[PDB]
Image 1: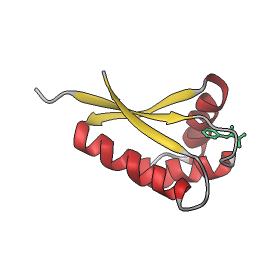
Image 2 (image 1 turned 30 degrees about the vertical axis):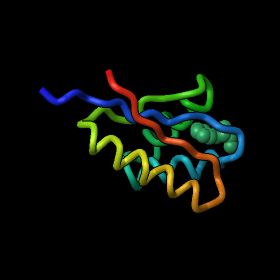
Image 3 (image 1 turned 90 degrees about the vertical axis):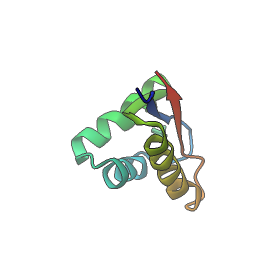
Length: 83
Ligand SMILES: NC(=O)[C@@H](N)Cc1ccccc1
């Protein structure tokens, strides 16, 4: 069976809180409330699981979300890691 991969949101000190939130809404189809909570989870504990899915999908979403921050001049980082 294909291995599943966690998409992780990593904290940083520069990306605006609300920007992270709308990234989460747009790329991972979260509500505002859910988005804030995941954002805040990473904010407090250094990181947060966003979603767990098939590798290629996990990689694609992590990059899409990362690029949004990157092209905005933010160090916002979404990574993948196996479970
Ligand atoms: N602007 C700030 O104070 C960031 N801690 C907000 C943030 C949350 C989650 C990930 C990255 C950034």
